[PDB]
Amino acid sequence: ASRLLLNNGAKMPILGLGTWKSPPGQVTEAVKVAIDVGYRHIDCAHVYQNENEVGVAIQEKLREQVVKREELFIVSKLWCTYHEKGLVKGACQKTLSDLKLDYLDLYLIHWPTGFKPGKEFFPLDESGNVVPSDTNILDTWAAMEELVDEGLVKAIGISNFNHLQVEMILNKPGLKYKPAVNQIECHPYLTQEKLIQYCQSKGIVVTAYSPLGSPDRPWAKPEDPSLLEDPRIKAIAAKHNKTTAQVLIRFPMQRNLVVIPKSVTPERIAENFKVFDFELSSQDMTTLLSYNRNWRVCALLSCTSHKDYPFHEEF
Ligand SMILES: NC(=O)c1ccc[n+]([C@@H]2O[C@H](COP(=O)([O-])OP(=O)(O)OC[C@H]3O[C@@H](n4cnc5c(N)ncnc54)[C@H](OP(=O)(O)O)[C@@H]3O)[C@@H](O)[C@H]2O)c1
Ligand SMILES: O=C(O)Cc1nn(Cc2nc3cc(C(F)(F)F)ccc3s2)c(=O)c2nccnc12
Ligand SMILES: O=C(O)Cc1nn(Cc2nc3cc(C(F)(F)F)ccc3s2)c(=O)c2nccnc12
Image 1: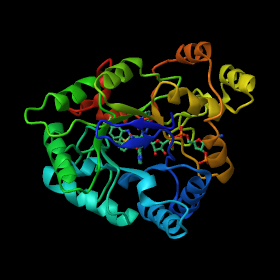
Image 2 (image 1 turned 135 degrees about the horizontal axis):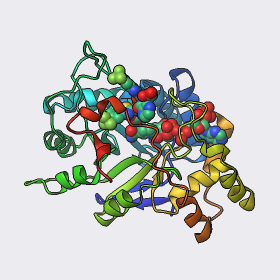
Image 3 (image 1 turned 60 degrees about the vertical axis):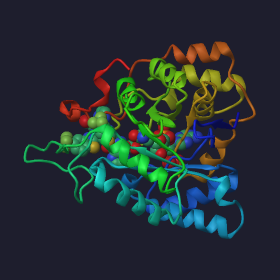
Image 4 (image 1 turned 90 degrees about the vertical axis):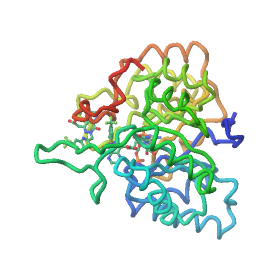
């Protein structure tokens, strides 16, 4: 279905527009186009450095009466340099001010790893490594919880958490709110079966990020495997008279995951939305699952030493 029910009673659109790497100068138009096309979910983050320009778009479409605020699902994310309890609210309000909203539909802990607070998104020490902060997930969660009580955000969740980190929150003594969502990298080369099964079992909705394999991530190398150019996936696409992107978007949807493909390109924003009028076969789904290779595009490998580095566990 086009929306999934969250554990807070809200309906989250299963298709949203990603905005990482969307430059300030193109993201306003992208969001306006997406909304015109019918997207009702935008995935944002402070660290994407474009929330102002996302805000401008939403304001215009509200003013044009193309959409109402309550038909939109806006997500943002608390960056790693703000995990200190006392900094969480300020970060949230700064995001709200930039987006020009009164509330977020969903606010996530962007990554489990706290970094040193300050002006830099990735504060480096003299060795050129990221500097951790003395912060922990449960205290950051407590501060996220307070945002709900204040009505700044309708829902809270986590992103890039492994199952033990999730369990830690679920088992917190005095827990006020379970995570609504865990947003994780997910595509045919990283199919995430075990963490998906775990989260779904707990009533936590999974959002699949980098569904097209993030070919525009700054660090892509030419030898890196490429989902959009995989001939196996094109053949499945051709069979439905759809594009490879459309298949890659449809795939998570049929696993009951939310998916958030990024484009600044109007024609592709439009293409990516045309995923409600076809269906992958159960054989197609099996096949796409068989392509897993535990290939991960977002992993900041030098953070392996951080106590909260998520990707040591099997899931
Ligand atoms: N929670 C997290 O830690 C996290 C991590 C990564 C991503 N995310 C979220 O997930 C979103 C999506 O992931 P992503 O941005 O890494 O990458 P992605 O959506 O897998 O891929 C985006 C890339 O695919 C291209 N593209 C889009 N539609 C296409 C189509 N129909 N045909 C061909 N190329 C197409 C885009 O080109 P153009 O823009 O040039 O059209 C862009 O280079 C992000 O933007 C962000 O919102 C979250
Ligand atoms: O490490 C590489 O060679 C490229 C690469 N980069 N990145 C992004 C970043 N990598 C870094 C690395 C540093 C640091 F300076 F090494 F600490 C500081 C900030 C960042 S942001 C990944 O997340 C990433 N994840 C998986 C694989 N490669 C990468
Ligand atoms: O975080 C996102 O939503 C996408 C994104 N990913 N990456 C790769 C990253 N990978 C990681 C990995 C960790 C980890 F928790 F240590 F594993 C912590 C922070 C990061 S950031 C960037 O370097 C990055 N840099 C700027 C903006 N966005 C990103």
